[PDB]
Length: 226
Length: 52
Length: 47
Image 1 (spheres, one colour):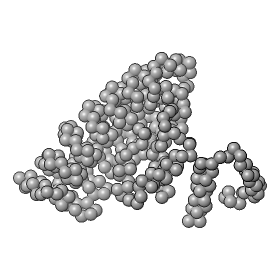
Image 2 (image 1 turned 180 degrees about the horizontal axis):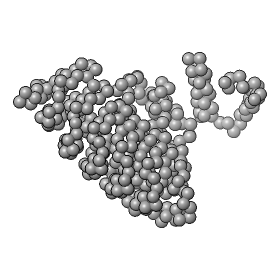
Image 3 (image 1 turned 90 degrees about the vertical axis):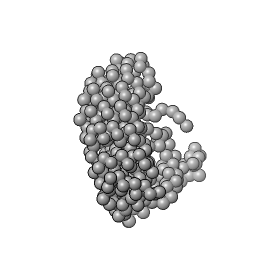
Image 4 (image 1 turned 180 degrees about the vertical axis):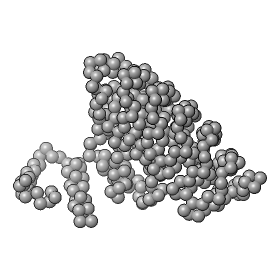
């Protein structure tokens, strides 16, 4: 069934996208925005989730801390990146929000930006001085998910910032291995032509040539020697 | 749910892999049948993972 | 039904793991599907 996503009134009002009642609530009491629910979130998070620009601009005008995190450590920037809204990202980054903030699994907003396949959000986030070589608790970059979801333009704009392809996962699987697992010819040939090392072995001791099927590793090696 | 992340759950089980995933999900349903929370979140999933 | 439980402070305290498991079973049973509007429970203890 459906219903209220939270016990707090201001959070449900922020999720419903009611501007006048929320503004009235703030004008009535200024401590309502500082309250916390069982999910340890504020109205700002649900507002960024709703995708309303006016509300979050008003809140950020009030000076509400963007560094506030929940029990799972989710930042408003992660929710904004997951929502696929450009204006919210413009507001948050415009207020000086930290791009180095990490959640429970330590995944940077760039990961969720490449997950929802949002080019503008990723570009704007990486423009703020973010590090594309940053690793999570699982020691994996956004290039992994980008190659896993089969996004050429994402990897391309990630390579516009000259991000290193030499990052090794704790499992031992390089983004090239994920590119071969996704059976993407263009992505594989591109990454290989960009100087990606195929000599990196995983815990399974499996070369990227053995990962791909149909003689794809053959033409990959052809691109290496060529 | 939007709070639920598929990244950590596509990551950690790749390291440590158990059996009967759907059964574990049903156990999480038994955790969510306690009427403490309307929408199931990553907490119930992680708990169901660490318990069994 | 009327339930009378005396001295429940003893059970209220892999050795601890099975105890926690039994507690989880109690939670599963009490929070499961049943009608409590009729059956009554009484608990006696010390501290």
